[PDB]
Image: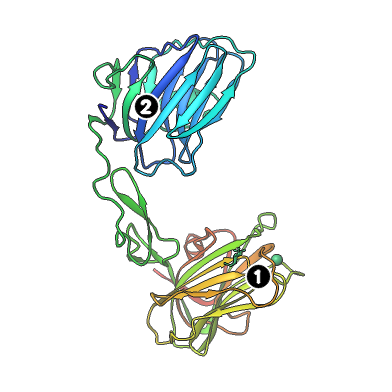
């Protein structure tokens, strides 16, 4: 009923104070693509307040009845920012039993030692003034407003028109639900990029593509390795050495060599764990160790030392691994022999193969490893990057 669109997070409306003194019943429907946003705020005397907000895609109901801030997490199997309509029901009875109903799932919670809820400010819907965020209750996570569609707002036998009954409107607000008209299709992002739906369009996660730009169509950061060999080393701050159950690696390359090491991830001294991306007999492959036997996975059918650009993508889950060159079928490997799951205490990323006795010659582009765009960081002179030998940035 009467959908209204908040086109930006910063947009909100202010209605007359919600009266929820001895009991409360709120209902509304929402539709959004964003993970975070303040949907509803009303404060009162002393520390009294209510808040409804999305946090990481989940509906949170935060409140203070006068004896301390409390949080109820609405129950859902999925995050709710899926561009689908969701029903939200929030009630409080006279004994202070709260109920939160998100679609079909019910969550209940009682507050002991509380009396009544004394709300006094206007009721803010969609967000608040930008300078209000800094004096929000500590338990409230929102630093920005809600973006999306609200409909059927029921404040307990009070059915306001969010536009006509508003005492104040801020920013871009319309009647109707103006959802995204350009939605994520299979070919929205190039080069196997992951399409992420936004409110006014889409963006692309290019992490595993070796490419950059808004559509994963632009060349990634590139270095060239020439005569004599070179090396780019990333060393983790000794305290921030990660240990992982799952690894993700992507890089683009061009070369004519039939033997070389491109990337090696090593654990610190006295530990045997490592991850190695290499070319053997003109075929790209990965060898790794997470505590027992070496595990090898190879694309044995694609000859990749033709001097043409290629993309390689590697995933590890415990002992399990996948490898894919370009658009060839994905290679899967499930270990022979017994295995552990953690890649312990990762200390260095060595790019160029010189120290491993297999120097790389050619170009490397858009290296990504567990959140780290390593070649980008080298280009931006990160303090944990060391570059030696015959290596240069393709500017
Ligand atoms: C590896 O693969 C097996 C078989 O599909 C699966 O059951 C297991 O959970 C996987 N292990 C890890 C650590 O992902
Ligand atoms: Ca290990």
Marked residue nearer the N-terminal end (2 or 1): 2
Pick out the residue farthest to the front: 104
**Residue at image location 72% in from the left, 73% down from the top:** 292
Q: Confirm whether residue 244 shows in the render.
A: yes
Q: Where residue 168 sits: x, y (%)?
A: 29, 18
Q: On the image, which quarter does residue 334 sit in?
A: bottom right
Ligand 1: give its quadrant: bottom right
Left or right: 113 in relation to 36: right
In the picture of the structure, the residue carrying the numbered disc 2 is 28
Classify mark 1 as within 8 Å of ligand 2 or not, answering yes or no.
Answer: no
User: Residue 194 in the image: x percent, y percent?
Assistant: 39, 58
Quarter assignment of residue 109? top right
Q: How busy is the neighbourhood of tag 2: few (under 14 within 10 Å), some, or many (20 plus)?
A: some
Is residue 95 found left or right of 78 in the rendered image?
Answer: right
Q: Name which residue lies at 41% across and 21% down.
A: 26
- Distance Cα–Cα, label 2 vs label 1: 53 Å
Image quadrant in which the C terminus is located: bottom left
* Secondary element at image label 2: strand
Label 1's element? strand
Farthest residue, direction right: 270
Residue 303 vs 157, above or below: the answer is below
Q: Quadrant of the N terminus?
A: top left
Which residue shows up at 27% across the image and 16% down it?
165
| Label 1, residues with CA under 10 Å away: few <14, some 14-19, many ≥20 | many
Q: Is residue 213 left or right of residue 359?
A: left
Instruction: Determine whether 365 is above or below 69 in the image.
Output: below
Residue position marked by numbered label 1 in the rendering? 266
Camera-nearest residue between 114 and 146: 114
- The residue closer to the viewer here, 203 or 335, is 335
Q: How is the model colour-coded?
A: rainbow
For the question of whether residue 139 can be seen, the reply is no
Q: Pinpoint residue 219: horizontal percent, then vertical percent.
A: 36, 68
């Amino acid at each position: 009923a009467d959908p209204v669109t908040f086109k930006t997070k910063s947009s909100y409306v202010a209605l007359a104070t919600l009266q929820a003194y001895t009991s409360m019943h709120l209902f509304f429907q929402f539709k959004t693509t964003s993970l975070d946003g303040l949907i509803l705020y009303n404060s009162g005397d002393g520390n009294d307040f209510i808040v409804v907000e999305l946090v990481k895609g989940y509906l949170h109901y935060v409140f203070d009845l006068g004896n301390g801030a409390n949080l109820i997490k609405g129950s859902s199997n999925k995050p709710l920012n899926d561009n689908q309509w969701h029903n939200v029901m929030i009630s409080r009875d006279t004994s202070n039993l709260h109920t939160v109903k998100i679609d079909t799932k019910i969550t209940t919670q009682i507050t002991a030692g509380a009396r009544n809820l004394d709300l006094k400010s206007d009721l803010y819907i969609g967000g608040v003034a930008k300078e209000t965020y800094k004096s929000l209750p500590k338990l409230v996570h929102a630093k920005e407003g809600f973006q999306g569609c609200l409909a059927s707002v029921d404040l307990n036998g009070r059915l306001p028109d969010l536009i006509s009954d508003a005492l104040f409107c801020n920013g871009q607000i319309e009647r109707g639900c103006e959802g995204p008209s350009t939605t994520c299709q299979e070919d929205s992002c190039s080069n196997q990029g992951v399409c992420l739906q936004q409110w006014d369009g889409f963006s692309c996660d290019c992490s595993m593509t070796s490419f950059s730009g808004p559509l994963c169509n632009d060349p990634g950061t590139t270095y060239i390795f020439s005569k004599g060999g070179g090396q780019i080393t990333y060393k983790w701050p000794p305290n921030d050495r990660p240990s992982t159950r799952a690894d993700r690696l992507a890089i683009g390359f061009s070369t004519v060599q039939k033997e070389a090491v491109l990337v090696r991830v090593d654990s610190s001294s006295g530990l045997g764990d490592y991850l190695e991306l290499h070319i053997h007999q003109g075929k790209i492959g990965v060898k790794f160790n997470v505590g027992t036997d070496d595990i090898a996975i190879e694309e044995s059918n694609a000859i990749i030392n033709d001097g043409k650009y290629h993309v390689v993508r590697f995933t590890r889950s415990g002992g399990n691994a996948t490898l894919q060159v370009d658009s060839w079928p994905v290679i899967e490997r499930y270990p022979a022999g017994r295995q552990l799951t953690i890649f312990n205490s990762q200390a260095t990323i060595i790019i160029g193969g010189k120290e491993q006795g297999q120097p790389f010659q050619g170009q490397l582009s858009g290296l990504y490893y567990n959140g780290l765009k390593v070649l980008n960081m080298a280009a931006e002179n990160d303090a944990n990057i060391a570059i030696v030998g015959n290596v240069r940035l393709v500017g």
